[PDB]
Image (cartoon, rainbow, N blue to C red):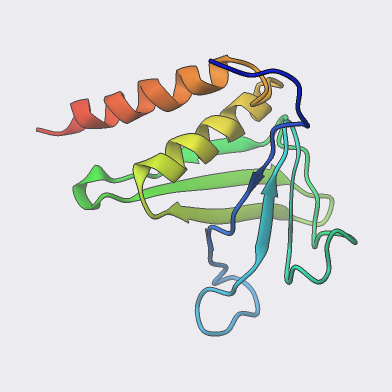
Length: 137
């Protein structure tokens, strides 16, 4: 690929977040999410940031369980992170496979210590896009 000199590769997009085991209204709530090489933090409202996120966690180590169901072009990612108070279970649902492969692949790379900066990143997005197709009947 064509790439020279630029800032660190970071993703900016608010995915689907739902927490039935906590004070919530109107189901989902608009929030600000940001994926970092080996880090991840979100906020309640763009206002907060860049100040400080609601709860920062080091992806490197957390768990990532795939919950996608091609049956209905659905792709969710269950991120399980340990907390000194309890746990950090966040449900992220993607609209399509594109956003999924991108984010998902990023989480895995961070969990293993790796980062999106690495080329392998794309190596995951592809393998996935295809894998899904295979699953089909």
